[PDB]
Image (cartoon, helix red, strand yellow):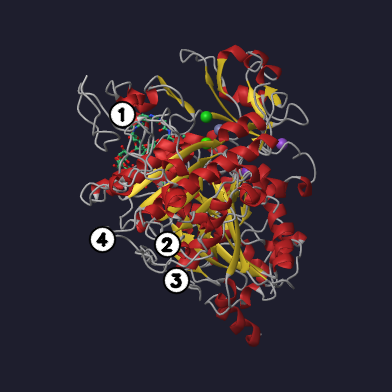
Amino acid sequence: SGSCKGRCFELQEVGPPDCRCDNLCKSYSSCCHDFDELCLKTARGWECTKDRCGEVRNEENACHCSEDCLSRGDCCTNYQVVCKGESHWVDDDCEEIKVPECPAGFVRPPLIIFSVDGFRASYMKKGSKVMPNIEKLRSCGTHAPYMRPVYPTKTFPNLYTLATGLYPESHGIVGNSMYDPVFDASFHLRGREKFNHRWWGGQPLWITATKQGVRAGTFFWSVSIPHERRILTILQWLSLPDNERPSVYAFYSEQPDFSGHKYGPFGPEMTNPLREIDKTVGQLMDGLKQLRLHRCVNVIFVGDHGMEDVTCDRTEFLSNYLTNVDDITLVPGTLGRIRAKSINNSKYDPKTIIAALTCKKPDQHFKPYMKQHLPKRLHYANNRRIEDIHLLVDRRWHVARKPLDVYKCFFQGDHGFDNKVNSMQTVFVGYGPTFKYRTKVPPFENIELYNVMCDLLGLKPAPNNGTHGSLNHLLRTNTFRPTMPDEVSRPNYPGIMYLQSEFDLGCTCDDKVENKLEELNKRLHTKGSTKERHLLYGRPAVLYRTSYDILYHTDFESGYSEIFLMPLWTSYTISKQAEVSSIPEHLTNCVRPDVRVSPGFSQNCLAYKNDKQMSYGFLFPPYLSSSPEAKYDAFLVTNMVPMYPAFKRVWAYFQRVLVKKYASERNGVNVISGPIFDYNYDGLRDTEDEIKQYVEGSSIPVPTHYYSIITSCLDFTQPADKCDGPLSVSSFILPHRPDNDESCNSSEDESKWVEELMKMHTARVRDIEHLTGLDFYRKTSRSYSEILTLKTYLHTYESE
Ligand SMILES: *[C@@H]1O[C@H](CO)[C@@H](O[C@@H]2O[C@H](CO)[C@@H](O[C@@H]3O[C@H](CO[C@H]4O[C@H](CO)[C@@H](O)[C@H](O[C@H]5O[C@H](CO)[C@@H](O)[C@H](O)[C@@H]5O[C@H]5O[C@H](CO)[C@@H](O)[C@H](O)[C@@H]5O)[C@@H]4O)[C@@H](O)[C@H](O)[C@@H]3O)[C@H](O)[C@H]2NC(C)=O)[C@H](O)[C@H]1NC(C)=O
Ligand SMILES: CNC(=O)C[C@@H](NC(=O)Cn1cnc2ccc(N3CCN(C(C)=O)CC3)cc2c1=O)c1ccc([N+](=O)[O-])cc1
Ligand SMILES: [Ca+2]
Ligand SMILES: [Ca+2]
Ligand SMILES: [Cl-]
Ligand SMILES: [K+]
Ligand code: NA
Ligand SMILES: [Zn+2]
């Protein structure tokens, strides 16, 4: 029982049990008794009217229209408009902000993050007639057509990602609700457990800023502080003296999410919440202008996720699938997470639950996954709060445990689904001296903003999942100049060193069936004469310590690892006019030793013969060889990789059918393909002592995934091998699995399911980099910033 007089919304939290007056005291029930009275005034609303102009100051009012209000910094945001003949910010023409236009004493342009909830990307077009303030920021500043959220596309995972640059698996906020089995505790959007710091990892922007001497309070706000008071509080803090005034601010809205859940993303009821949000942006913008800061402050208008049509009747029930549904706990809704109801149960079987949920109903509106089998693009596995069993739920559907969980309809909207889904996409607009003027930028991921916000504030970012430099094109002036990571391992270039009779690999090939214009041509090819043709962007750099060989061939070049006994990468180009052939019958099972590489660093056919589960495929496909003579190169033991027969069905369709179709559609393609090892599902390259599976009785390690990166010219009138402008890329990371249980239609012809599987497993080049320790596109004519943007690109396969 102290007092909040003169202390209203103090930035520093005061020591217990002395009462608090900061923006969080209400959450902790620890405000002074007069907090409401002094700090949450509402009298007379939030607008000046003419009759108030030059009033005698009445300290009980929510805001002021008295002559002294500018000096005090507590005018209603519309004061100068209603009482001084001034115009609303939205009514001013927009004028380029070439330099920061800040009052004396401002050391840097302030950053204000304006965060909207459930603000679906398409609201920017569809709601344009009712959001004039937001439409002005959008067209005058720098904007993307949409921004991709993290998965799950829920509120808390995304807001903390925005603040950290980290995937939820890394920052720890992996859901709106979660259970930590080490804490034996549950975090919920509502309640006080979330106040415990033990849930929150990484280093949020306000901590980064503080550690480096830039003032910034926490971004959290007590729920019962309304939005008009939040704006007035930011505007007040902006009037503090230089030595006390923060440089970063965050405002968060409950809308349009609150209404969208009730009404659907496009319910007629949705127009008003969009109007109210625009009005709030108007208030902030008029207030900034009153403080002469509207050409000084950088403003970020950003959403956390979109919103989809979802109703009670579109719910799948696990009780329709599982006989023993009471033995599980489900995190339900737009995603599913399943764990044992009771830990003291060795009669709980994840494999049997998964099998009972797999392809059981023809139209089944969810798919089960062990978390490590989820598409790697989701980066959703490496945290103990993520249950081993995950259900990816179709857009527009829910999953629930039992029917009484849903009837004990409330809602018409929800969000949470896979982050590639169009309806889950959200918004980004940057406006201010440091952002560009009237500029559209390509869609990008919210994990990249932490770095940009650090650049906006002169800060060195904490280590995070953004790729710093990838968003330099948003900025008029950047403090960050990216440079390529240095190569750690230089390759060996072996010559012909071994005779055939030194190998005992138990391999066979029909190849003895045997000119100097042609023979000199074949040795030129083994020495890299065609390398300009098949390695278009230089060779990848190896960023870790290892031993490997560059191997040249007429059709493909490779980086062959002597430690993993297989290529780390295989690079080749297939022109639009290139032709597909078959494997001649006499070479069906041909494998040939490579006289450049020792028996001791080679795979062997015997292991594959003995391993009754594991077969093999090739990284450069025999099917695409340029000539009957070159085809022999494709059967080298150095081009071979371990592959489950079930996976060979996928890979063979990709190599025999899809590669050629891409070359026809894209006017040639360059392909880089290779294995990935990620047994501990942390998204990062495994070292050799982390490998859990080998081909039986050998040291040949088994990949968890195979990747390919597929590059051509953005201008497809030019061929892939003669491109002088920007590049186009799509990539995938395919799980290397011994069954096709993921694909419910896999009994059918590959043309009915393979491409669908690959699209699900689409990836950024940067994801493959993390997973292999390789750095691509080292030698192009493109700027490094442009290449970094290319490496973060995801081909989504969604409609427009
Ligand atoms: C996305 O970007 C992040 C950030 O760069 C990368 O994460 C880093 O990975 C490296 C290599 O695996 C880790 O290094 C290890 O660090 C530990 C000591 O770790 C402690 O100290 C660090 C640094 O101050 C701290 O950040 C760590 O925080 C983890 O654990 C906390 C509590 O246990 C938790 O609150 C927090 O969320 C975080 O959890 C996550 O990471 C851990 C692994 O560290 C993991 O078990 C957990 O499930 C979560 O995923 C920690 O207290 C050394 O002893 C090791 O030898 C090793 O050097 C970094 O710790 C790690 N940092 C963070 C913030 O996660 C990702 O790899 C990158 N992803 C991709 C795909 O590139
Ligand atoms: C309209 N929407 C909003 O206002 C969104 C806003 N919601 C809240 O702040 C709701 N709330 C209310 N009182 C709290 C009191 C204490 C805490 N702990 C958390 C852990 N601590 C740390 C880590 O410092 C100490 C403080 C949290 C809260 C809290 O979440 C929000 C902003 C940023 C982020 N974000 O994730 O960045 C998430 C959530
Ligand atoms: Ca939200
Ligand atoms: Ca790993
Ligand atoms: Cl959740
Ligand atoms: K076999
Ligand atoms: Na199947
Ligand atoms: Zn919501």
Label 2 element class: loop
* Amino acid at circle 3: Tyr
Nearer the observer: mark 3 or 1; the answer is 1
Residue located beneath label 2 in the image: 469
Label 4 element class: loop
Q: CA distance from mark 3 to mark 4?
A: 62 Å
Residue located beneath label 1 in the image: 38
Residue found at x 44% / y 45%: 162
Residue 493: assigned label: 3
Q: CA distance from mark 1 to mark 2?
A: 46 Å
Nearer the observer: mark 1 or 2; the answer is 1
Residue found at x 33% / y 53%: 461
Residue located beneath label 4 in the image: 104
Looking at the image, tell me whether mark 4 or mark 2 is earlier in sequence order: 4
Looking at the image, tell me whether mark 3 or mark 1 is earlier in sequence order: 1
Q: CA distance from mark 3 to mark 1?
A: 77 Å
